[PDB]
Amino acid sequence: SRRWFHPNITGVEAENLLLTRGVDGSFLARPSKSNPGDFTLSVRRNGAVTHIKIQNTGDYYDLYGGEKFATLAELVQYYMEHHGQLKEKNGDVIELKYPLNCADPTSERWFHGHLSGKEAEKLLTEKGKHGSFLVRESQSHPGDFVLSVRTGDDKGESNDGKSKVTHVMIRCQELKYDVGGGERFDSLTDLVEHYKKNPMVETLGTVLQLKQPLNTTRINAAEIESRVRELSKGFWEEFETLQQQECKLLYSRKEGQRQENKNKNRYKNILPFDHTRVVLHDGDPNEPVSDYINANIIMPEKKSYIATQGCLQNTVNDFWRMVFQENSRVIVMTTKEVERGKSKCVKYWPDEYALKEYGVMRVRNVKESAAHDYTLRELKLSKVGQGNTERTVWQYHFRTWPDHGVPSDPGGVLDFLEEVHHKQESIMDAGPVVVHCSAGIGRTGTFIVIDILIDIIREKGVDCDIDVPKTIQMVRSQRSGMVQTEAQYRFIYMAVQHYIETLQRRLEHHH
Ligand SMILES: Clc1ccc(-c2cc[nH]n2)cc1
Image 1 (tube, rainbow, N blue to C red):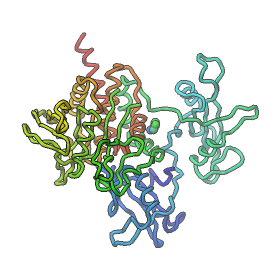
Image 2: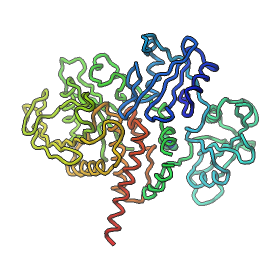
Image 3: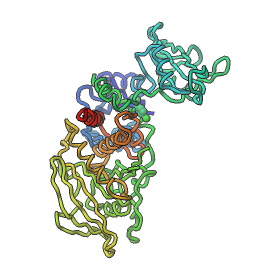
Image 4: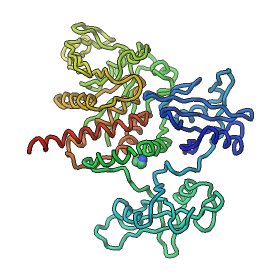
């Protein structure tokens, strides 16, 4: 689980907790109160506490005096299975041995805090199904909580009486929680987990199975403006609830962790999941391992994507092997080659009108066209020795994304993605759209999620269901950490709103 993240704790509270309820090797992580994208790892050692800063401006989590990570949970797993790996400024070793668990329930999907019983019934009546549940505050008994559960036959329709809502009072007595007998638990989370595993039964047989929380994030796309107004007064709480679910996604990354593959990775701990990695065939027999690239297939769940990193000097040939094998006809690039004086994506294309060989692959730059926010390069890709393999690959290079943060208006991103979409759709049997640069998780995830959400509205028009955090979770299950920050999360909502709003202007302008 992810109980070592404390969403609402001050530095002084962090110290107190470690000193009175922890030991040497106890740790926790907390967000900074004022400056978002800043986090702190607090750790006890030698009877004192040290605080280690973690920064995220949109590309990765950067731990001072340590490494860069795709998620906070991947960071914690790495140092809990690797001792003496984290070092102080002095040079000494910092051990993360014992998570210090949080009781606060405000980031759990099942917690509704403020709710009443009839409101909860109508919610579960309308949006909920067999085994749907929530926890809420009591109105008769101050300090207590209530667990509310729908059960019965989902097959049924109409108001037949084949389903019901059951309410179970939860008492809180000196910092512990219980359902009126048996075991006393240290947090609501512990209590919910236990009765999720060991469901309560009623005197007459009904089993109160806790199968899934109630969904409160799905909206009709035409109501986007109302949700955004409401989240603006919010976006942080919804984001951090989504982040709590990242512990479910620690899938294996063994092929990336192999010796033979180590210097094919921009950052050594940001790696592709095994189950979705792009596998390269037809390699050099002599090369020991010719089948690896730091890239994943992203399938929405008819257009698919490949999310990948900026090339290294020694992976440019592999990048073109991938584009050729997968039959990709469109590449999206989300960084300048250089930002803040550091290399972000190596130049892997020829100058305009020039021609270059990259291993067995040949590329001609036919023509570049400059737009306000991007440059388009018309490339032709073929295998050396075989003329009939030539196909056009169109490269869309987004150039105006800010060095830190996100753009303050989404129009340029949306016009860009609309043009990428029409090109892709013009080409019979095109393979997946390649999206990259930097570590290939932050901007890359943001552009893919926006594209997925807009495509639904392109198909089904302005009245249809969208669910931003649920989409991000499904994409995060196919590459680590897709969408990095609160500001990117907000930006996604704003882009959908802008899209909906222009689409309604067609109808206004018509009448
Ligand atoms: Cl799959 C999923 C993950 C997270 C949420 C959520 C609900 C409130 N915030 N985030 C909803 C669905």
